Image: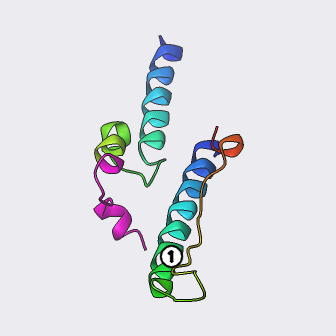
Amino acid sequence: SSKSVANIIRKTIQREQNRIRMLNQGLQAVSFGQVRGVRLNVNVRESHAI
Amino acid sequence: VERDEVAAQKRELEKQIERLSQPSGAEDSRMIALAERFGGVLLSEIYDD
């Protein structure tokens, strides 16, 4: 059960990262003042990865 | 002798039960590494539902 829980957490994290990366493509090259692009950076915290 | 025979049957039963356990019951002994090492998905899991 613990192994399954870990695997499902990993799978959900991967899916959400993929979805956010997909969404990010639409905000490429937005010209606002000196701002030229916007990104939602998603990462896995080490304190929780371990 | 009866106890050992029953124990052998038992061990076979738990091995069979485990073989269907994770990630989706299959030849997970090496199928796991063979599956995540490459950007693919198990066919059985693909037809899981």
Position of residue B36 in the picture relative to residue A7 (left or right): left
Position of residue B34 in the picture relative to residue A28 (left or right): left
As drawn, A34 above or below B39: below
Expressed as whole percent of the image width and height from the top left, the position of residue A16 reads 55, 69
* Outermost residue to the top: B1
Expressed as whole percent of the image width and height from the top left, the position of residue A22 reads 45, 78
Residue drawn at point x = 31 percent, y = 44 percent: B31
Of residue B42 and residue B21, the one placed in the foreground of this image is B42
Check disc 1 and give the amino acid type.
Answer: Arg
Expressed as whole percent of the image width and height from the top left, the position of residue B14 reads 49, 35
Secondary structure, mark 1, is helix
Which stretch appears magenta? Answer: B35-49
Residue drawn at point x = 61 percent, y = 52 percent: A44
- Residue A20 lies in the magenta stretch: no
As drawn, B9 above or below B30: above
Instruction: For mark 1, name the chain.
Output: A
Name which quarter of the figure residue B29 lies in: top left
Overall secondary structure of the magenta section = loop
Of residue A7 and residue B45, the one placed in the foreground of this image is A7
Name which quarter of the figure residue B15 lies in: top left
Residue drawn at point x = 28 percent, y = 44 percent: B34
